[PDB]
Length: 134
Ligand SMILES: O=S(=O)(O)c1cccc2cccc(Nc3ccccc3)c12
Image (cartoon, rainbow, N blue to C red; front, side):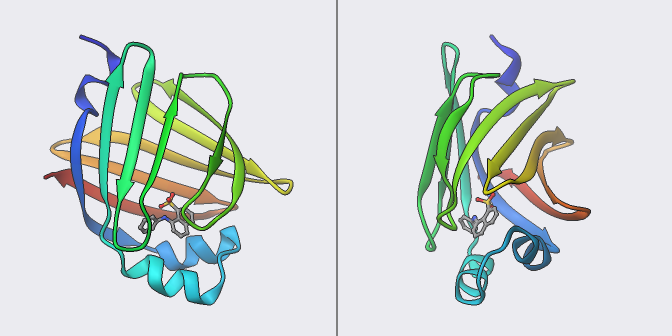
């Protein structure tokens, strides 16, 4: 067993709050905001050794990242940002920082009851996206 044991599995998006405002703060354009905001992605989390993989499948785009905690990697996000990402485990919460164009956003993923709660933060604007097991 390992730390991420309660994160592993397939998760389906069940609610979203403030995601359009979060996307605006990130700089996402109108058309991408409309189409991306409609999507109801799944999140598939798996662990193999020290490598964590998070896949997101949706009608908008399919993305996948694999990474080792604390080790920076390149990520092309669903909205086509080329970012430098570092993901760590802080007190049981996966903390994902993305840097690009002098900007920064943080995505936190944590277990709460039977939910996986994803909090996306950009300059004082937060979006909460709640997932439950598929
Ligand atoms: O990757 S997320 O961190 O959510 C994300 C973060 C910030 C901006 C985003 C803009 C468009 C789509 C996303 N993802 C997305 C992917 C599939 C379906 C719907 C939205 C964005």
